[PDB]
Image (cartoon, helix red, strand yellow):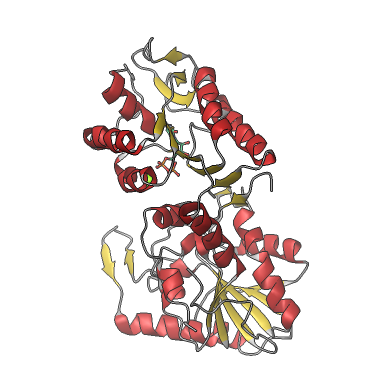
Length: 403
Ligand SMILES: Nc1ccn([C@H]2O[C@@H](COP(=O)(O)OP(=O)(O)O)[C@H](O)[C@@H]2O)c(=O)n1
Ligand SMILES: [Mg+2]
């Protein structure tokens, strides 16, 4: 819903300084970006600004959850700066803080065409407006300090842009408290909301949802809301053992069992049933002797049970084939969460096999949407997508200027 908000295509940025909230919270290992998808997604708004005559583009984001303590040794945005520079073909001035004297001066009037990335916002308790101390307790933020944090951010540009879709569910100071006459939705913000609004309000049918993940209790709302829209639905990952234990009394050994979500499984199945949704659960498995990448692997079916002391970490071949048949009937697919422990090659086969079917479906004309160009749309969303789909309002979209 961006018919009534100001958006970038209309903002005149010529000779103007631009502050842009983006989502550069990327997955990392050992100070190394493991996935630069969130960085690439931000490129077209940045380019447009630079191309249209921007004095400067100042970029701000969080990374991980450092809970209002500075952690530049574990959670620094510096690695992103180096990545952004290559992608952009431009120099990137990395600043080691996000508010204050040094930052405001550095951004006061940069050389024409400067791209500037600030340090992790969540190094300041005032970004969330709450935090944890070094003894792990409930530290309250100070209103006067929040007003100062925000007022410092409002200095780094003449105009504001939110291209931060992956964070749009967060009412944080960088997301709703920036004070400037013009607050615009960037091109990503627009692309994301257009794909998910078309997918949900004029779906191509048959419409398939694939939902995977570890726990059930936290997806009740998602599943319910999806169950009113979709023609089919796959339920996969460690969340399916809860389902199979209740609907089939499968012996799951040490596989994950959501004791709470177990009590409403019945109601989900009942609403699916009355709505005519076909529920596709896994029927076989790759089992492991412990929660380890280098565990000993086995195999099991619903008929056979998983032996005791062993746990299920990936669906198997016959489950793969079942998933594929739903993929074949679909004209639209929304996929959220893995069907197994794809992190680990031994347990990655189900997700790979499945990605292939979804890719092949795209070639025939299926609209395929996956969570954060072989598919229609790879979302940066993940957690914000889930809230989009639970029907809830996005603090990041609501705070943009009205026309
Ligand atoms: N036994 C298990 C354990 C984890 N998982 C997957 O569960 C995913 C995360 O669980 P989650 O529900 O808390 O988060 P999402 O899948 O919604 O992103 C991890 O990426 C694992 O690959 C699984 O499918 N089966
Ligand atoms: Mg969750």
